[PDB]
Length: 203
Ligand SMILES: Nc1nc2c(ncn2[C@@H]2O[C@H](COP(=O)(O)OP(=O)(O)OC[C@@H](O)C(=O)O)[C@@H](O)[C@H]2O)c(=O)[nH]1
Ligand SMILES: [Cl-]
Ligand SMILES: [Mg+2]
Ligand SMILES: [Mg+2]
Image 1 (tube, rainbow, N blue to C red):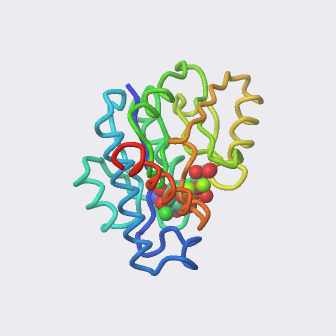
Image 2: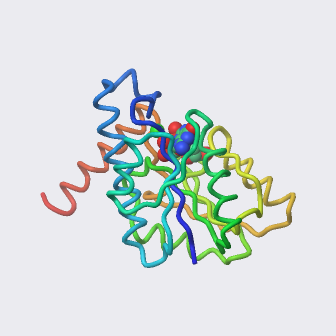
Image 3: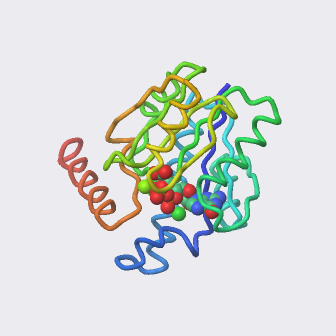
C-alpha cells in the first residue's frame, strides 16, 4: 500500500541551475521529459498503489494527469521539503500506510530501482542518495516517522532524524537512483550514459 509522491515546480521556473547552459525552452523540454519518465516509471510499477504529484502549475498538472498521477495543489517556491510534507500530511490524514518521495529529475529511474527501495521494512526509513552522497533522491517511510529535509545536505539531515527517533535505515545506492539532473556536470553525466547505452544495447 505505497503512495508515490513526485513534487514538481512550474515549468517556466524549473531547473534554474541549468540557465547558464540551456535556453528557457531547452529547460522546459528536459523538465517535462524527465518528469513524465519518473511519473511513467512509478505508474507502471506493480509496487506503487497510488501516485500523487504536488505542483502549483496548471501546465504541470495537465501533463501529470495525462501520465496518470492524481494532483495536490501547492504554493510556488516552497521547496521540495514543504511540498513533500504537505503531501505526507494529506496521505497520513487519509489512512496512507507508506509513502515514497521521488523527485521528477531522475532520467535513468527503472522498475528495479522502485522495487529495491520498496523492499525497506515498513518500520524503517528507506533512503537513496545522489551521486556526491550529500543529497536524497528517494525516501520511503510511514507518514509522520521523521520530518523531511530535502535539498541541501538532506542525506545527513534524514540520517540524523532517523538516529534521534531510533528508527532503522535502509540505504539504496545505484546508478538509477543517484543521478538527478540539477547542474551542468549532471546533464553531461546523463548525456554520457545515453551514449554508453547506444553502444552497449545497439551499436
Ligand atoms: N511542488 C513543488 N515542487 C518543487 C518545489 N521546489 C522544487 N520542487 C521539485 O522538487 C524536485 C527536486 O528539485 P531539485 O531542484 O532537483 O532539488 P535537489 O537540489 O536535487 O534536491 C532535492 C532532493 O533530491 C535532495 O537531494 O534533497 C523537482 O521535481 C522539483 O520540480 C516547490 O516549491 N514546489
Ligand atoms: Cl525543477
Ligand atoms: Mg535534483
Ligand atoms: Mg540534487
